[PDB]
Image: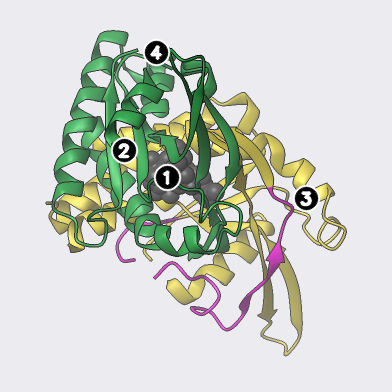
Chain colours: A green, B yellow
Amino acid sequence: NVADGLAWSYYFGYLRLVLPRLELRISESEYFRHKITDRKLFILLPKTCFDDIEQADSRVKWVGNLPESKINRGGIKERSYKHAVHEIVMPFPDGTEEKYHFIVEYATPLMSLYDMSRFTDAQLTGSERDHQVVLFIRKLTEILGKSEECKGRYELIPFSGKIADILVALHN
Amino acid sequence: NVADGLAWSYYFGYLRLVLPRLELRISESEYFRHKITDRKLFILLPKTCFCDDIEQADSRVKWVGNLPESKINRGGIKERSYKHAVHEIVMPFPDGTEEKYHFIVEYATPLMSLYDMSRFQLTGSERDHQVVLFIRKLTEILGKSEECKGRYELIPFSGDKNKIADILVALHNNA
Ligand SMILES: Nc1nc(=O)c2ncn([C@@H]3O[C@@H]4COP(=O)(O)O[C@H]5[C@@H](O)[C@H](n6cnc7c(N)ncnc76)O[C@@H]5COP(=O)(O)O[C@@H]3[C@@H]4O)c2[nH]1
């Protein structure tokens, strides 16, 4: 499957690298370390969308990035791996609000699957793309479920194209 | 195929973004703009065996710095950093002389996950076939890409680990 290769590469080539570094990168962020509501990476997995999170939910906006990890990989001495912090503002019946700060990003391989459906040379119809997205979510779920270094450091968020509601509910 | 998804992702998520920017990043480098004359990304494609550190493998290859980074809003990450490294090659010649070259060279990172998929549900011969399919598909993708034309060189090789400098200098001289 196309999705199985994208899922394993997403683990070996990214999550396995950054998730063991996440807590250290947070603690180095003088601006965010005391603000971060939850110390996990929230990975958005839209099934029919597509990459700006604010355009998916107006209550979520980017406010800053964590300090980058510099990793020697692929002949690149200091390749940059950094996460983004997003602020969630939940309006209430009182007319009041309450703010949260989450480390959240889209699953990047899903963006390539969408790009593969917009070019016929990639041999991916819209129907086949939606199936491969589901296969990607399932394979990535079982890979991370058996991971030692990533244990307790992530949260997968599959949804159909509400994000702020899901994130706030999961934190509670 | 597994290799087809990795090749398309390598194009849509990287090459299609950085190759149209490469010329500009080179010209923005005060130190490297006149030292790098092959203004293209040399992509190493190890086929048989595969460490990813280029400079410790060959005493003639040394990392001497980075180009200016490209910043692209992507996947919810604002200003995600895409940056190339520059390697200096000091090539001894048979007559005792030395010649100095500068290259933008890097490994095709998706191949690293293919080797990781095997050395930790993919047999060795299955990996070798998927690597071959990745190279073929990537060659086809880039051959039809107008925004990547003249900006790349694909280098399939065994993985000769201490022969990269020989391969790069030969390719510069169109050998
Ligand atoms: N959110 C996020 N931030 C990152 O820094 C990151 N780096 C990789 N990935 C995703 O993990 C998976 C495996 O990574 P890999 O390096 O093998 O392939 C990458 C890699 O070969 C190349 N590439 C992308 N960015 C860079 C970069 N900055 N330097 C060198 N190569 C890069 O193009 C491929 C696809 O990139 P992405 O399409 O962004 O998704 C990747 C991929 O799905 C990332 N995802």
Residue bearing the label numbered 2: A171
Please say if the residues under marks 2 and 1 sit with CB atoms less than 8 Å apart: yes
Q: Which residues are magenta?
A: B45-69
Q: Chain of mark 1?
A: A
A119 or A40: nearer the eye?
A40
Query: Which class describes the residues within 10 Å of circle 2: few (<14), some (14-19), or many (20+)?
Result: few
The residue under label 1 is which amino acid type? Thr
Residue bearing the label numbered 4: A120
Residue at x-position 18% and y-position 39% = A141
Residue bearing the label numbered 1: A37
Question: What is the CA distance from the residue labelled 3 to the residue labelled 1?
Answer: 41 Å
Q: Chain of mark 4?
A: A
The residue under label 4 is which amino acid type? Thr
Question: In front of the other: label 3 or label 2?
Answer: 2
Q: Mark 2 falls on what kind of element?
A: helix
- The answer to whether tags 4 and 2 share a subunit is yes
Query: Which class describes the residues within 10 Å of circle 3: few (<14), some (14-19), or many (20+)?
Result: many
Question: What is the CA distance from the residue labelled 3 to the residue labelled 2?
Answer: 45 Å
The residue under label 2 is which amino acid type? His
**Does residue A166 appear left or right of residue B80 in this picture?**
left
Residue A150 is one of the magenta-drawn residues: no
Q: Chain of mark 2?
A: A
- The answer to whether tags 3 and 1 share a subunit is no
**Does residue A130 appear left or right of residue A34 in this picture?**
left
Residue bearing the label numbered 3: B26
Q: Earlier in the sequence, mark 2 or mark 1?
A: 1
Residue A93: give its label.
Answer: none
Q: Position of residue A172 (x, y in %)?
A: 28, 36
